[PDB]
Length: 60
Length: 53
Image (cartoon, rainbow over all chains, first blue to last red; front, side, top):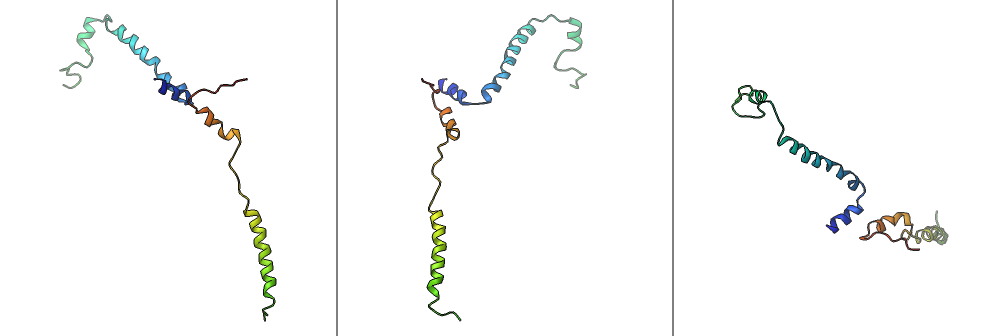
């Protein structure tokens, strides 16, 4: 790791830009946990399931 | 219309010319020593620069 970060030290732009995609990881970490237990309407889940098979409104 | 004795005068002229050329062309530009041209050689060292005073 010291070698990689010693090269990051010598970079000029990537060491100040490539980290701006990292907050997005924590965004996913938080939203996933929100979604693992999200309460939803049974009627809406039975009428519009997301990417479920054999839905004629999708085509198959 | 050109005698043979007049030749060494022409040779002297051309020697003067080529000597004026070669005295200039004998000079050459050495290696650059400006620190602004080589500061990135020190920026890219494996360790940070120590400003020691």
